[PDB]
Amino acid sequence: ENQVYSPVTGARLVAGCICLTPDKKQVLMITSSAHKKRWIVPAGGVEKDEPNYETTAQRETWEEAGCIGKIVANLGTVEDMRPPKDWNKDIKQFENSRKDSEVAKHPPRTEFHFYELEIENLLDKFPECHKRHRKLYSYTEAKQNLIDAKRPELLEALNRSAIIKDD
Ligand SMILES: [Cl-]
Ligand SMILES: [Mg+2]
Image 1 (cartoon, rainbow, N blue to C red):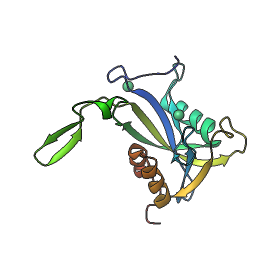
Image 2 (cartoon, protein in one colour; image 1 turned 135 degrees about the vertical axis):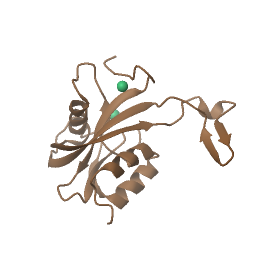
Image 3 (tube, rainbow, N blue to C red; image 1 turned 120 degrees about the vertical axis):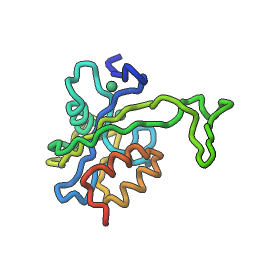
Image 4 (tube, rainbow, N blue to C red; image 1 turned 180 degrees about the vertical axis):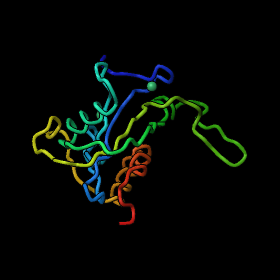
């Protein structure tokens, strides 16, 4: 009940961090709680008492990854546009035009506010350290992880960061 939603779309409001090594060659990824083999980035729900998205982003990066660092860029917003739960059993799932197909119009599940963080430390004891793994990946590896995880919005956020892409 401490969760915050868009007053317009009803999307859950979430913040998180693209956590880069100081040399900008790697990004910190974490395993999903539900799916141990899916690698994503730290992010979670804004809570009602939190004054800004940076606070949520750095809290969730601590809770989920045991990562501390400095926010160095605002990477703006991305949206989880996965269709609702009922979607694949509904009668009209797609809206087609002359040269294009789209999933039927729906609000986003989640609106993510992403920041780029420069990693200053990784701690062995952190709140979710027995529920998740946290590991550095090159850009090429991280991109494949996020496609494997079916989270293109997280890849959109990563691509806005200063991560070195030509591995
Ligand atoms: Cl909003
Ligand atoms: Mg979360």
